[PDB]
Amino acid sequence: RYDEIIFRKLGSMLQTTNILVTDDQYNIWKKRIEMDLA
Amino acid sequence: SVLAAANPIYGRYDDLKSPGDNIDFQTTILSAFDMIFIVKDDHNEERDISIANHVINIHTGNANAMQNQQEENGSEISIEKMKRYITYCRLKCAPRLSPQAAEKLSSNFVTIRKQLITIRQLEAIIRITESLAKLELSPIAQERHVDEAIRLFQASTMDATSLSEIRRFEQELKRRLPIGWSTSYQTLRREFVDTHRFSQLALDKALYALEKHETIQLRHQGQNIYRSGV
Amino acid sequence: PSYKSNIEDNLLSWEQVLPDLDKIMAPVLGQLFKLYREANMTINIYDFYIAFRETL
C-alpha cells in the first residue's frame, strides 16, 4: 500500500485509526463463519 | 615428528598485525614448520549454541552411547583399533607421487609465488599428499589428495587473469571509498556485485588483499569496513 | 514530531515519500546523504566529489 503510508507519514486525519477491527478482517471472519453456518 | 602448540604474544592474536609481530621467538622457526594454524574464536550466535549443545550432551553422558552407536555403524573408529590401523599403515606401505599431482602442485605454487612462502613450501606440501596416500595405502599419491592438501595449506599458511580484475576492484574501491570513511560488506555487495561491476570472488579477494596491504580494515565480522590507509 | 529523525528517514527512505531515468536514480540529496553518513568528521571535498561521481 502507498496511500496509507504517505497519509501516516504526513500525519493526516484521513488515515483510519486501528482501534476497531479492519473492514477486510471482519468481512473475512463473517464470511468464514457464515459459510459453515448453514 | 613435532607437534607444537604455541600461544601468540599479547594473549590474543591481533588481526591488524603481521604474524611476525604477534610472535616472540626466532623468525627462522616460521621457516621450520610445514604448517601453522592461527585458530580464531570470534564470538558468534548459532555456532556457540551448537557447541554448547555438544558440551551439554557430553556432560550428560549421552556422548558415550552416541559414540558406541557410531562405532557400531562404522562411522567412528575405536582408539585402540585406530592405533593398530596407524601402525599397520606405517609399517607396510610407502607411496610415491604421480606426474598428474606434481604438475598441478607446480602450477598452483607458481600462481602463489607470483601473487606474493618459499620453494620449500611446495616440497613440504608433498608430505601431505604422501601422508594421505599412506592413509589410503594407495601405491601412489593422487591429485584428489592434492586438492585437500592445497585446501589445508591455504587455510593454514594464509591465516594472516582474475588478479587484474581484483586490482581493478581495488582501484575502484580506492576511488569509491575516501580515506577515513566507513562502509559495510553488504553495501559493497549491493553497489558493485549486484550491479555486476565486479564478481563476488573478486570482492572477497580484493578485500583480503587490501586488508593485508593496510588499505582497509574489516570490523565486526564484515558488518563494518574502514579504510585505514591509501 | 521527531523533526530530525523524520528528515533523516526521508533522506534514507525516500521510497516512503515518492510514489525514464526517474525509475532508477533516487534524488541527488538522499544519495549524497548516504555518503554523508558514510563520511568522516572532516572531508577533503575533492574525494567526496570523486566518490559521488563514481556512484552516478
Image: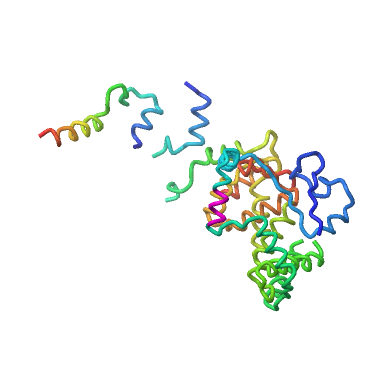
In the depicted view, which residue is nearer to us: B47 or B90? B90
Can residue B45 be seen here? The reply is: no
Residue at 82% in and 66% down: B120
Work out whether B141 lies above or below A17: below
In the depicted view, which residue is nearer to us: A24 or B107? B107
Its colouring scheme is: rainbow
Instruction: Say if the magenta span includes residue B26.
Output: no
Residue at 27% in and 28% down: A22
Q: Magenta segment, which residues?
A: B66-72
In terms of image quadrants, where is residue B55?
Answer: top right
Q: Position of residue B11 (x, y in %)?
A: 78, 39
Can residue B77 be seen here? The reply is: yes
Which corner quadrant holds the N terminus of chain B? bottom right
Q: Position of residue C6 (x, y in %)?
A: 49, 28
Q: Position of residue B78 (x, y in %)?
A: 63, 56
In the depicted view, which residue is nearer to us: B49 or C15? B49
Residue at 76% in and 58% down: B35
Is the stretch drawn in magenta largely helix, strand or loop? helix
Q: Position of residue A15 (x, y in %)?
A: 32, 26
Residue at 76% in and 43% down: B13
Q: How many marks?
A: 0
- From the viewer's perspective, is C35 left or right of A33? right
- From the viewer's perspective, is B191 left or right of C47? left
- From the viewer's perspective, is A1 left or right of B187? left
Work out whether C34 lies above or below B32: above
Instruction: Say if the magenta span includes residue B68.
Output: yes
The residue positioned farthest toward the bottom in the image shown: B99
The residue positioned farthest toward the left in the image shown: A38
